[PDB]
Length: 357
Ligand SMILES: CCNNC(=O)c1ccc(CN(CC(=O)NCc2ccccc2)C(=O)c2ccc(N(C)C)cc2)cc1
Ligand SMILES: [K+]
Ligand SMILES: [K+]
Ligand SMILES: [Zn+2]
Image 1 (tube, protein in one colour):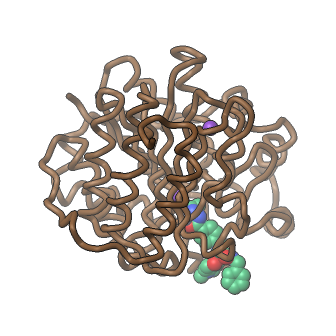
Image 2: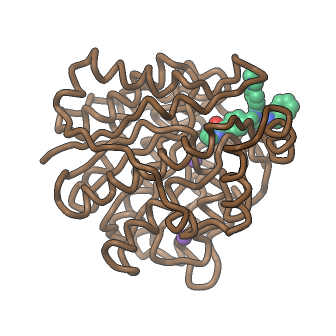
C-alpha cells in the first residue's frame, strides 16, 4: 500500500493581477505542501510528477470553443485578460492561468493512472486552479476546466468505458459543472454535500437541490445533499455519510473514488460558514477508503483559510497512508435542519437504491 502525492509549484503562477488579496491565492497549494513536509508526511508518499493535460484530453468534457478561448488567454495582455475574465461568473485570469489549469488536470491524470495500474493504492493532488464549477462550455467560480470530471473520463479511457467512478464532492459549494457533465450517465455516480440555503448560496441555482436525481439512464446517479439554515459540522457530515453516501456508494461499488476535496466547509474558512474539523475530514477519508479496494484520489478544490486547509488536507493524507482515524462522537445530535435535509435526500433516492429501502 503506497500513497501517491502530486504537487508542482508552477501552479502558483495563476494569480489575480487586480486583487492580490483574492481568496483563491497561489500560496494555498504551497502552504498545504509545506504542512505535509512539517508533519513528515511527504517523505512517506511516492511523488507522482505533474504534467500538462492535452487538448484532446480536455475534449473529454469540454467544448472546442471553450478550450480555444481559455487557450488564447496565454497570449493576452492585462486589459484583454480583464475583459475576458469579466465575461464569466467569478473568474480572474492571468497569462499563466491556462497552463496552470492544464497542470492541475494532468497531475490528476497521472495520479489516476498510478492508482489504476497498481503503482500506488491511493493518492492526493495538491492542485489549483480548482475545477468543479467549470461546465462543458464555460468557466465559472475560480474554475476553468473540470479537473475531477476530466479525471473520471481519463480513468475510463485507460481502463474501460464502463469503469464505475464515484465522485464525492465535499467542497462547501455545489459542483454544478460535475453534476451537469454526468447528469445522464450511470457510469459516474456524483454525490455532493453543499451549503444550499434554498438556492441563495453560490452558485445560486436550484440545480443543487435534492430533487435533481439525474436524467435518463442517469436517474439515481446524481445525489445532492443540500444544507439549509445551520452551521453544519462533523455530526451532520458523519450522519450524511452513514445514512446516504456510504449505503449508496457500497451498492454502486465503485472501482475508483475521486474526491472533489474542497476544504471550505472547514472550521475557520472565511467564506464557507461551516465547521468541519480536520478530524472530521479524516473520518470521511477513512470511510471512503473502504470503497473501491482503497483506490481513492483526493483532489483539492476550494478552501481559503491557509491553516485550515493545510491541517485538513494533511489529515486526509495521513488517513490514506494508513494512520488510525481519530475517534469522534457519533451520538452528538444533529442540528434540526440537517435531519430535514437528510430525510429529503432519502425520499428522493429510495426509489433508485435498494440499500435505502
Ligand atoms: C471552486 C471551489 N468552490 N467554489 C468556491 O469556493 C467559490 C466560488 C466562487 C466564489 C465567489 N463568491 C460567491 C458569491 O456568492 N459571489 C456573489 C456575491 C457575493 C457577495 C456580494 C455580492 C455578490 C464570493 O462570495 C466572493 C467573491 C470574492 C471574494 N473576495 C474577493 C474576498 C469573496 C467572496 C466564492 C467561492
Ligand atoms: K460539494
Ligand atoms: K451521474
Ligand atoms: Zn467551494
